[PDB]
Amino acid sequence: GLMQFTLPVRLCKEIELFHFDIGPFENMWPGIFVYMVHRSCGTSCFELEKLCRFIMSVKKNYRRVPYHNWKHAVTVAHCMYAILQNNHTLFTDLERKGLLIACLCHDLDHRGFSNSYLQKFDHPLAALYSTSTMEQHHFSQTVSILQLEGHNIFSTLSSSEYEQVLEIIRKAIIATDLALYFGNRKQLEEMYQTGSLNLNNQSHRDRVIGLMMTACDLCSVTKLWPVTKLTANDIYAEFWAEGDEMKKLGIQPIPMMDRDKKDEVPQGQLGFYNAVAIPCYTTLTQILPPTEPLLKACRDNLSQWEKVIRGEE
Ligand SMILES: CCO[C@H](C(=O)NNCc1cc(OC)c(Br)c(OC)c1)c1ccc(N2CCOCC2)cc1
Ligand SMILES: [Mg+2]
Ligand SMILES: [Zn+2]
Image (tube, rainbow, N blue to C red):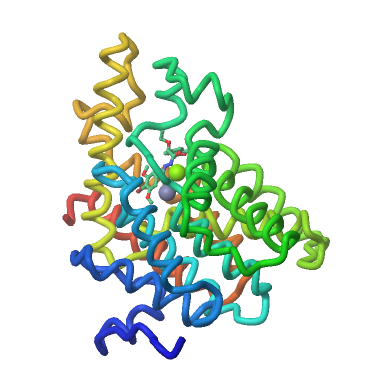
């Protein structure tokens, strides 16, 4: 009950900033997550015994792939912690509870392959979940872990709070399917600009939480340049493996996934910042003004990829 996690001084300070990197020490990541849940939610939100057992089972169900791994899960959870901490009064108790868990679980059992590759391979998950294939799997895996003896961190919720929190998590995890982000953002953009955006309207809140999920999921583009540039290597390591696996099915992959087309990456990065990242953090910042540091960092990284193209690095 009276047992806080405490971090060394430098982490205690920098964990509060959007651009925090969780570090190369894997054994500190469970503690960093519990710290964030205690400050975001409270010491009371979860039985520590049950939370620790949940965290360790989630970690076991992330695979040893270059990007869609345990480090990504915790990184995406930290970006949500920082949004939630800078927007204290906008979010219910259930939402703070659900959203940190959803971010931790949102890529559970990822194999390093897109929804597209599962469909072309004719993977069994693609027959079972014809859209948002991996994300429906990630939610399926979150529910399975929650039902292991000892792992039900929501045990002290009432029956209807429990239904609400699993519904928050389901929607939050489905929204990390980037194919859905484009229309979600367009709708939020119209709503904000015509002044119809209403955070008491559940369907509106759902959309705002979806955009928060995309912003957290993409948050490697909001880090200091050296972190963003080194993370891009892991992201492309997966893309190029999937490219190779497309060529093995006798499909020419898109250039982004072709390791023979590495020279095209810096221009690919501009496309990605201008069509996905910048607009995501721009709309987020219009809806949640204190998340402006994520947009400012994203703009700095765009300017760094511009320098790469101009051979200034
Ligand atoms: C099967 C690949 O699909 C990915 C995806 O669904 N997510 N991409 C995530 C991603 C994250 C990221 O950093 C956190 C970086 Br850097 C990144 O780099 C490309 C991609 C995707 C990549 C580029 C686009 N373009 C981009 C150009 O405009 C249309 C959409 C659309 C989808
Ligand atoms: Mg995902
Ligand atoms: Zn993710």
